[PDB]
Amino acid sequence: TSNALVTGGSRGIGAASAIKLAQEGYNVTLASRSVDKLNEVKAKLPIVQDGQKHYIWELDLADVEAASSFKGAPLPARSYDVFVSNAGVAAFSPTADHDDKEWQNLLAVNLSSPIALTKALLKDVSERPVDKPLQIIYISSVAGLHGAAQVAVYSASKAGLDGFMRSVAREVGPKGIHVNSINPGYTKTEMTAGIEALPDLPIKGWIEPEAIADAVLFLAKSKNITGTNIVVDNGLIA
Amino acid sequence: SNALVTGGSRGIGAASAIKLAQEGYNVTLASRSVDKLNEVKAKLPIVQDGQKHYIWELDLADVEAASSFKGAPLPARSYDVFVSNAGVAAFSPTADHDDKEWQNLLAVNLSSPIALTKALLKDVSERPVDKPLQIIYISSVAGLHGAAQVAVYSASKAGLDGFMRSVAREVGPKGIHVNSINPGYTKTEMTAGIEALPDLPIKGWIEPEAIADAVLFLAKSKNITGTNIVVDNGLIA
Ligand SMILES: NC(=O)c1ccc[n+]([C@@H]2O[C@H](COP(=O)([O-])OP(=O)(O)OC[C@H]3O[C@@H](n4cnc5c(N)ncnc54)[C@H](OP(=O)(O)O)[C@@H]3O)[C@@H](O)[C@H]2O)c1
Ligand SMILES: NC(=O)c1ccc[n+]([C@@H]2O[C@H](COP(=O)([O-])OP(=O)(O)OC[C@H]3O[C@@H](n4cnc5c(N)ncnc54)[C@H](OP(=O)(O)O)[C@@H]3O)[C@@H](O)[C@H]2O)c1
Image (tube, rainbow over all chains, first blue to last red; front, side):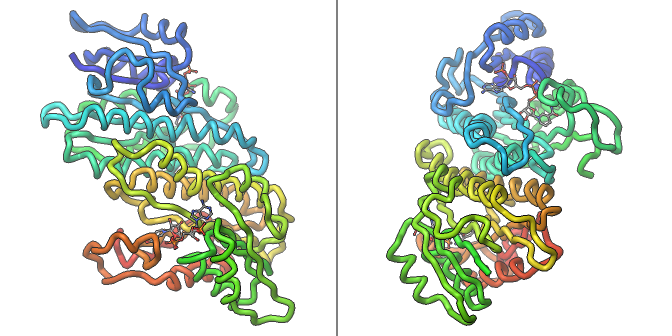
């Protein structure tokens, strides 16, 4: 069996990534706060091989100690072959006005919980064989790569995740653990539904979540990629 | 007029405070250590009539203290230069790094700088042309490339830089310019434990005064915002 953990599996990029991973034969564990929405995604996931099975994990990533301990998880951390750290929350505000508890919670969900989950996986896995590396894939953002007004703390969270990624990649490559970020541009999901007009881009229009999922698959099957960013942004930052 | 330097008690911050005071700024030194802050304060040049220096006992593990300028000798709007210098380092295998420890590191290195920044932005008078407010983060090359066993440290410094770029775009039109300096291996108490250097293009340790020269270049600048000034002896070239 192969197992993939997708946080934020209840909709958007995570749901799309989960579907594609299940089509490739992975047992997928969907993790988020919403049991009913998780179950609905679970019901749509492909089955491509007998014995394949999917799981849900009720997990609030505002709770960093739960992440750290894999609290409630259906399988031990060492069972996973792919970890798609996809859960995140956005916030649009003048920096002067952004409520302190709101921006601190954003950091906990976007940066501290991924850190804690990664630590828990590294501890349990310890090392991997050369034929079956563990792939850790952060869903970061182009906001971590260039400055956009009124998304400062969000940008901090994503740039921070990418900085963690490069250091972990160098540390654990010799253990057979490969670690990368995908940095999406404007992608049509619940998170960006409040945006009513896009910037003028070299490739026009919204990106679909399924397009980000194809980049997850590219990394999940990869062999010689670690410590890098895969930017899927319609040319926003070119 | 006024410069705020967090982590003013030693190292890069102390050297930066000395150079800013040489330039005529009234310097506020902030850190946890009132006695060491007073020792540095006594060494700060006085070069201009009416010039005055201050200390501020501030623990950046307390993010709400930062956010409210708790205990500050001057309001946030009085500052013309903000050197966000305080920071802490930690070395560990990621798998074994104590949760309270790495969370406290994020608070000191990232969340408190964000909070001090928000306080300054909220209080400031939009700035005249020849007197922009300069915000200068002391980040690290660790935030630009991957080094093993400093993962959460690297996350803090990369996060600081991502914050910096977004704030720069946002507040430039208010006359507020915002940049990071990313040092390499510098001779301070932070590095006294870890001595063999890598094989560098420019050999040897960097002096804290050398970082302070970069602070002064930014403090006097006019057309720089959203960027990184890398002073690293060629480590990352
Ligand atoms: N859409 C874009 O334009 C775009 C661009 C760049 C990057 N991203 C990144 O893409 C990732 C996925 O976002 P999305 O665009 O697919 O938006 P989305 O459809 O709103 O998905 C957000 C996901 O995160 C989960 N989540 C949020 N807060 C959580 C918490 N406290 N604990 C557990 N799970 C939580 C949500 O599940 P529950 O609500 O069920 O808990 C949901 O499954 C995010 O990391 C985001 O920053 C998005
Ligand atoms: N040295 C290097 O090679 C190097 C390289 C890259 C970046 N840096 C960065 O340079 C900055 C300055 O460090 P340094 O090398 O000059 O080290 P240092 O001499 O040890 O100085 C660190 C300063 O930070 C203050 N600080 C630490 N924790 C604090 C807290 N909780 N509240 C308030 N102040 C606190 C310390 O003052 P108290 O102890 O008095 O509170 C001290 O003044 C740091 O941000 C560091 O990450 C250093």
